[PDB]
Image: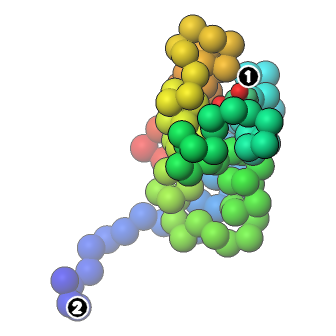
Amino acid sequence: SMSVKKPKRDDSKDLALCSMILTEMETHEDAWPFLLPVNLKLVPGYKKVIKKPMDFSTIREKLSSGQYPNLETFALDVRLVFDNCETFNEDDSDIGRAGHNMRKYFEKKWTDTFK
Ligand SMILES: CC(=O)c1cccc(O)c1
């Protein structure tokens, strides 16, 4: 509260560490469904169903331009990618499996890096 401060995380390396995690996700072999925005003109139903599209290239642009105020907003956008994937794809499809795989991959890097 006012004039009563908690000790807080050293956050000075957060930007660089998130960038490294994102690089590891960008280069994963199962990243291909998530590298670019889904083409809303070519993919029936996506525009109406998925209220907040997100993809790795949009996250990278946002990270490179100071649009994440903290590491938690970065993780929210990453998770949104996989939450969207689950919404639109069956678990046993190729894209569906890729999403589960990439989510697992992310969360381990996230825990190992920050928790
Ligand atoms: C990420 C996703 O949900 C996707 C990507 C390409 C084609 C498609 O139908 C869906």
| Foreground residue among 69 and 79 | 79
Question: Where 25 falls versus 102 (above or below)?
Answer: below
Tell us which disc is closer to us: 1 or 2. Answer: 1
Residue for point 42% across, 64% down = 9
- Residue that carries the numbered disc 1 in the rendered image: 30
Q: Position of residue 26 (x, y in %)?
A: 77, 37
The image quadrant where one finds ligand 1 is: top right
Residue for point 73% across, 54% down = 58
User: Which amino acid type is marked by label 2?
Assistant: Ser
Callout 1: SS: helix
User: Which amino acid type is marked by label 1?
Assistant: Asp
Residue for point 63% across, 44% down = 47
Question: Where 75 falls versus 45 (above or below)?
Answer: below
One can see residue 102 in this view:
yes
Q: Is mark 1 within 8 Å of ligand 1?
A: no
- Residue that carries the numbered disc 2 in the rendered image: 3
One can see residue 23 in this view:
no
Q: Is residue 29 left or right of residue 14?
A: right
Report the residue that reaches farthest toward the top. 92
Q: Position of residue 109 (x, y in %)?
A: 57, 35
- Alpha carbons under labels 1 and 2: distance apart: 48 Å
Closer to the chain start, of discs 1 and 2, is 2
Q: Quadrant of the C terminus?
A: top left
Q: Position of residue 75 (x, y in %)?
A: 52, 49
Quadrant of residue 36 within the rendered picture: top right
Q: Residues within 10 Å of mark 2 (few under 14, many from 20)?
A: few
Q: Is residue 72 left or right of residue 63?
A: left
Which colour style is shown?
A: rainbow
